[PDB]
Image (cartoon, rainbow, N blue to C red; front, side, top):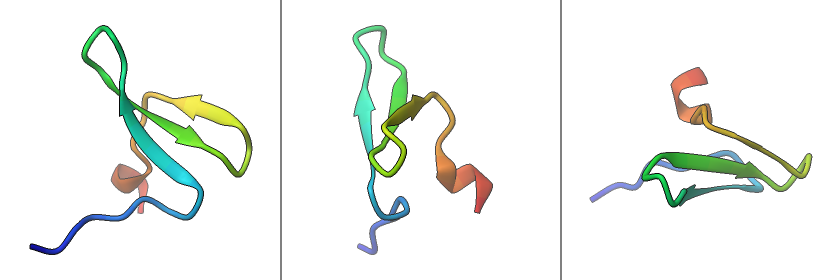
Length: 39
């Protein structure tokens, strides 16, 4: 039941076209690439 965390200031949403996307509030930017693939 352990959750997988994004780094601080990041959140995931689902776009209307069905793709997940990621908001980086630290830089006020968005990306299709999940940071967790990049740890």
